[PDB]
């Protein structure tokens, strides 16, 4: 159908869409005790994301061919998410990329970042990490400055430690970044968990 063709074209035209859809699918499927407002906003985000890429969700749902039987009025968001994931695989998406995005999303859900995920903010954060933080031969003095506004936009990741307090505990030592004391968990989260994942992602 035209839905699949639109999606197929949108995917090839920008790798960003695959990443954005992976976040939405993985947030829906892995968020814990999701409330109705969460389900409502995830559907909204999916529609905004697909439409901004030029495709209507309805045309895509038509190609999904969910049944559509029988004991409910309307199509559940759960079924659409499940069907979109099925369709993506059928379109032979890069699952190394998908799975890395899903792993990042899971980690972020654990850090109470759902509210910012629902805004669509996660892809910008991934890009910020890829280009400003987890870089080869990056200058620690510059990264330490850049990391500050990056974390300010996504404070859930600080795990309750204040921003200024964190940076009182991040140093340049022997030419490398050093996350000490109360900043050590953030340092490990970035260097050992997120940086390897963002290396797997294409954005």
Image (tube, rainbow, N blue to C red):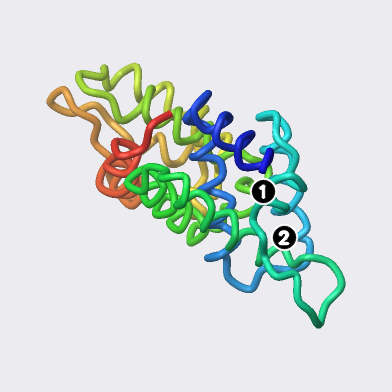
Answer yes or no: do the residues labelled 1 and 2 have beta carbons within 8 Å? yes
The part of the image, by quadrant, that contains residue 25 is bottom right
* Residue drawn where x is 30% and y is 18% of the image: 141
Mark earlier in primary sequence (1, 2): 2
Above or below residue 50? Residue 40 is: below
Identify the mark at residue 118; answer none if there is no mark.
1
State the CA–CA distance, disc 1 to disc 2.
8 Å
Q: Residues within 10 Å of mark 2 (few under 14, many from 20)?
A: some
Residue 100 lies left or right of residue 120; in this view the side is left
- On the image, the x and y values in percent for residue 45 come to 71, 45
Residue 133 lies left or right of residue 21; in this view the side is left
Identify the mark at residue 38; answer none if there is no mark.
2
Residue that extends furthest to the front in the rendered view of this protein = 1
- On the image, the x and y values in percent for residue 153 come to 58, 35
Q: Nearer the viewer, residue 163 or 84?
A: 84
Residue 77 lies left or right of residue 129; in this view the side is right
* Residue drawn where x is 63% and y is 46% of the image: 116
Residue that extends furthest to the left in the rendered view of this protein = 174
Identify the mark at residue 37; answer none if there is no mark.
none
- On the image, the x and y values in percent for residue 124 come to 53, 31
* Residue drawn where x is 29% and y is 36% of the image: 199
The residue tagged with tag 2: helix, strand or loop?
A: helix
Q: Nearer the viewer, residue 185 or 135?
A: 135
Q: Residues within 10 Å of mark 1 (few under 14, many from 20)?
A: many
Above or below residue 106? Residue 170 is: above
Residue that extends furthest to the bottom in the rendered view of this protein = 71
The residue tagged with tag 1: helix, strand or loop?
A: helix
Q: Nearer the viewer, residue 157 or 2?
A: 2
The part of the image, by quadrant, that contains residue 50 is top right
């Amino acid at each position: 159908g035209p839905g699949t063709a639109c999606l197929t074209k949108a995917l090839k035209d920008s790798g960003d869409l695959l990443v954005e859809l992976a976040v939405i699918i993985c947030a829906y499927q892995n968020g814990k005790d999701l409330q109705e407002q969460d389900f409502k906003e995830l559907k909204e985000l999916l529609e905004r994301t697909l439409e901004r890429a030029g495709c209507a969700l309805d045309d895509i749902v038509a190609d999904l061919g969910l049944e559509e039987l029988l004991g409910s009025i309307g199509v559940s968001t759960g079924d659409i998410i499940q069907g979109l994931y099925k369709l993506l695989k059928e379109l032979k998406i890069d699952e190394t990329v998908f799975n890395a995005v899903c792993d990042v999303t899971k980690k972020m859900l654990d850090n109470k970042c759902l509210p910012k995920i629902l805004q669509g903010d996660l892809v910008k954060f991934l890009k910020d990490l890829k280009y400003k933080v987890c870089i080869e031969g990056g200058d620690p003095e510059l990264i330490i400055k850049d990391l500050k506004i990056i974390l300010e936009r996504l404070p859930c990741v600080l795990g309750g430690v204040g921003l200024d307090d964190l940076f009182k505990n991040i140093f340049v030592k022997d030419g490398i970044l050093s996350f000490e004391g109360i900043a050590k968990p953030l340092g490990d989260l970035l260097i050992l968990v997120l940086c390897p994942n963002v290396k797997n992602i294409n954005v």
